[PDB]
Length: 45
DNA sequence: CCTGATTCG
DNA sequence: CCGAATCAG
Image (cartoon, rainbow, N blue to C red; front, side):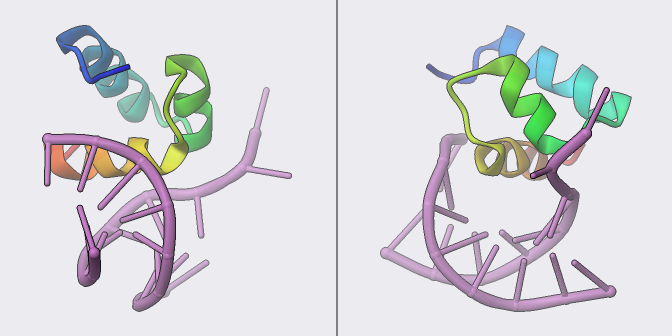
């Protein structure tokens, strides 16, 4: 499991949609909510 | 419909 | 860069 352009694309949409980090981690899968907050922070979303 | 931000290794 | 471990409201 890695951060593909698609998986980052999915992450972009949902974080902007206002979903909690745990819900986001749930849909993506194979990634803890910690890692989600980590990636968002780096992209400055 | 179970916090996010920021540091740390 | 990554995600766990802290920091912070």
